[PDB]
Length: 237
Length: 184
Image (cartoon, rainbow over all chains, first blue to last red; front, side, top):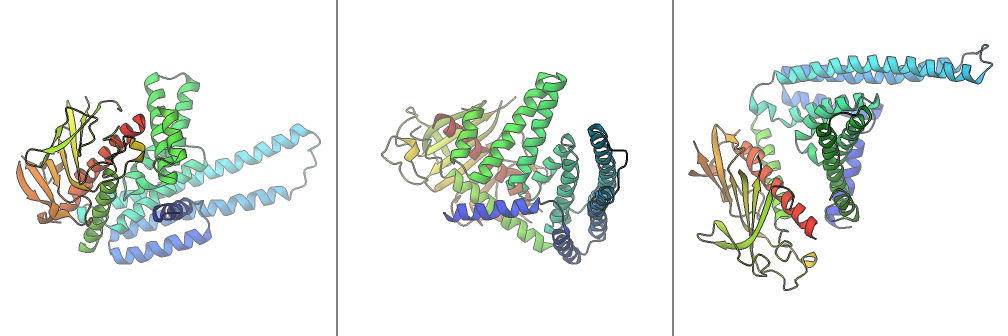
């Protein structure tokens, strides 16, 4: 591979890791770095924004532990009134509904914390402070976790304004997952217009934006004038 | 503080460099549109800051690309001036990049404000040199007076490349790319 192809391969893997579903090793790495950045930044509103962001991610981590424990406790129950196939499926559907409703509440609490993290960053008014790598790192982490929290629950239309705000920050526009999620969420919205028989202007708006971010994600991962880039361009043209 | 300002300037210098490295590739269009985009082939002319469209658009001796962007009036213009002649081979799929001698851009509509003034013209006289080429970027200011980007305080200098120049370099690289892909 060339120096650009090797660099690109390395970067796509780092970006896929960046958007990895949360776990304990990523949590530890993320917050230890954010606290070191907070000490460098020495800004009380950034400190508060981080305290809230961490509380939001903690809500998510608490839920992941709850879901495993809940499913475990249910698995260990004896079901005496489960003689029929429809009884087994019904009980399964009831389990999934309880899990989804609890995940929905955890998402709502996590987004209230993320909203507070943003409201504190909003209080940093000095343009020299809003341009801080520390400011941009935290703001990117808040939006990324916010996008993922909604994405997991299939709340794709809600991810669009946050993905858009995300890609405007510190070259995030060059991230392949960011364009993949935008393209998928736009695709969902296009399908909503087709299913609900909505207006043509919105059909084409959503289709257009899907194709822009589909092609851009392709360009970023495979490169300009790659068999894959040429293919997507030829489908669009 | 000033540390972050320094890092921001460096990232912006590199972003304008990476796109200028892509813009130098549009030589592939000399031997060769998306809606509201008009491309002309030509040569550097007059005082060396402007591009004169060819009578023969397909001519092998064109060393400048002039691209006009319209929307709903003319909104933007870019002139890519290249160092060196084109390859003799008539097939654009075989053509190689040429370092840019200059990039000249104009903003007519959707004007950006830098400290409340419009920089309507940007003249980059070393687009493929060291990324840190602020002294090679002339700024023509309207409230058009000539300023040098390297003499701009810094946020200001950062806002110039973040809000005006990088974005125009990227917009035009994308338009030149669309034209190339559509005819390639």
